[PDB]
Image (cartoon, coloured by chain):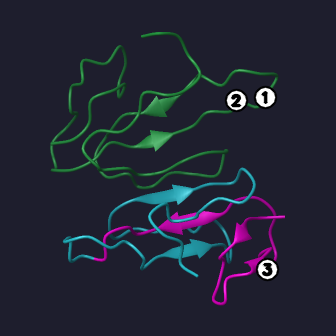
Chain colours: A cyan, B green
Amino acid sequence: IVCHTTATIPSSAVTCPPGENLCYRKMWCDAFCSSRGKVVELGCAATCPSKKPYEEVTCCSTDKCNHPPKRQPG
Amino acid sequence: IVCHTTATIPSSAVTCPPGENLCYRKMWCDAFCSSRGKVVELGCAATCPSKKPYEEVTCCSTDKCNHPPKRQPG
């Protein structure tokens, strides 16, 4: 009873794989900052893995969660 | 070059340690969501290892990032 949004491909809620609790998110400006932001990754497939590498991140877990403000993935 | 909020106490905008980027947001809902929600974390201390699973987390880096909700006109 995780996140009803994208959480993998033809985004249409998923409701995760095994688990319960948290929706995790990452990335905002692809890397060529000169305005977009619709190249993302939102959902859950395990242990708020967390992650590492780039800019913004998030270990949501309050209902639904991640609709990329600007737009929306799909 | 980061953050101006809490982040190791009374806050003085500091802009924490060394490195170059960010300040680590973490926390909020005690474990008594018997209302409110205001005993946080949100400082800095090297490299947002990321952290753990208690509710609410992240890793901002957008200039600044943390002063927290509900509250009173200052």
Residue farthest to the top, as pictured: B73
Q: Residue at label 3? A: A17
Q: Are marks 2 and 1 in contact (CB under 8 Å)?
A: yes
Residue farthest to the front, as pictured: A71
Q: Is residue A42 visible?
A: yes
Label 2: chain letter: B
Question: What's the magenta region?
Answer: A1-30
Q: Are marks 2 and 1 on the same chain?
A: yes
Label 1: chain letter: B
Amino acid type, label 3:
Pro
| Label 2 crowd bin: few (<14), some (14–19), many (20+), radius 10 Å | some
Marking on residue A3: none
Q: Residue at label 1? A: B33
Q: Is residue B28 above or below residue B11?
A: below
Amino acid type, label 1:
Cys
Question: What residue sits 52% from the left and 10% below the top?
Answer: B72
Position of residue B67 measured from the top left corner of the image (x, y, whole percent): 42, 27
